[PDB]
Amino acid sequence: EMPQIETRVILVQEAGKQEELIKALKDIKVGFVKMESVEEFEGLDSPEFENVFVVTDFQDSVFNDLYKADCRVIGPPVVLNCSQKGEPLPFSCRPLYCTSMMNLVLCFTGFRKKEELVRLVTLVHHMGGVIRKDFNSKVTHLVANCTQGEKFRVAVSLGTPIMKPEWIYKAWERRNEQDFYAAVDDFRNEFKVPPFQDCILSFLGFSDEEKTNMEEMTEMQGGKYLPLGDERCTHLVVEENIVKDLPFEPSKKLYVVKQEWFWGSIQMDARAGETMYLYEK
């Protein structure tokens, strides 16, 4: 314990009414008080306690209120969960609604709009994950991301989960779910980046059955495919064998891979490092 004083929960507005809650505070020997108005705030400064305010929903008005006062805020879920798992109040620099994303470490690549980033960044925080400027080992459960990228490239080579922004929002929706944690395999799965995102493909040296099976798969691994030779292709795959050589010519930034890169990427469940399959001879 670093604050040298007994902790006390304030139940803010309609939180006061929520029942299972009180029973939980009582359940974990923590004293509460209630508060309906932001004027009542003044008389809550008490030498006897450090105050933790429970808010029912960020953001009621009262939320950006308490924030502005720099005080310690939390969501109902954080509490019940302490009574359920027989815990003590957790601490963090920031408001904490629940605990879905305790204690992952996230990282972002390919975001061009500030507003949205922040929104994500807040949500994680509430949940409450942390973020890292720089991609390293400590990065948990997560690169939140849009497909081309230098840390994406890395994250691939490490086998650390790459996630769609939707992961977060769809996780924040389950904020009031009891034993819900957002790194669980299945939920992670629904929301990872599909091996072929922002990918458009074409095939060479293949059976109209083999091929038309691949096409089927590509659209299914989140990719899109196009009739050969289009300029809007990202990569193009070959039978490195059967093709002793080639019919068309590419653009600089189009890819010319070997058969394996395709299944590699799928057995991997993540886009794969192209440099390794680049075509020669």
Image (cartoon, rainbow, N blue to C red):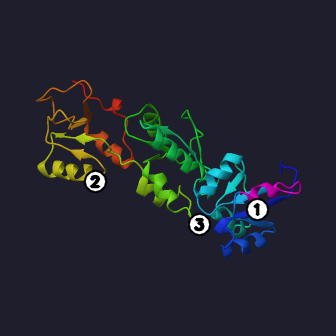
Q: Measured from the top left, where is residue 231 in percent x and y?
A: 17, 32
**Nearer the camera: disc 2 or disc 1:** 1
Instruction: Kindly identify the amino acid type of the residue bearing the numbered disc 1.
Output: Val
Residue tagged 3: 179
Instruction: Kindly identify the amino acid type of the residue bearing the numbered disc 2.
Output: Met
Q: Residue at point 56% right, 59% down?
A: 181
Q: Is residue 223 left or right of residue 226?
A: right
Task: Answer yes or no: is residue 93 visible.
Answer: no
Q: Which segment did they paint magenta?
A: 39-50
Q: Measured from the top left, where is residue 3 in percent x and y?
A: 84, 49
Q: Residue at point 39% right, 40% down?
A: 146
Residue 173: image tag: none
Q: Is residue 278 left or right of residue 69?
A: left
Secondary structure state at the residue bearing disc 3: loop
Q: Is residue 42 magenta?
A: yes
Toward the front, the furthest residue is: 39
**Nearer the camera: disc 2 or disc 3:** 3
Q: Residues within 10 Å of mark 1 (few under 14, many from 20)?
A: many
Q: Is residue 211 left or right of residue 144?
A: left
| Labels 2 and 1: the sequence-earlier one | 1
Quarter-of-image position of residue 5: bottom right
**Nearer the camera: disc 3 or disc 1:** 1
> Residue 39 versus residue 142: which sits nearer the camera?
39
Secondary structure state at the residue bearing disc 2: loop
Give how far apart the Cα atoms at labels 3 and 1 are. Answer: 23 Å
Q: Residue at point 80% right, 61% down?
A: 8
| Labels 2 and 3: the sequence-earlier one | 3
Q: Residues within 10 Å of mark 2 (few under 14, many from 20)?
A: few
Residue tagged 1: 9
Q: Measured from the top left, where is residue 99 in percent x and y?
A: 62, 57
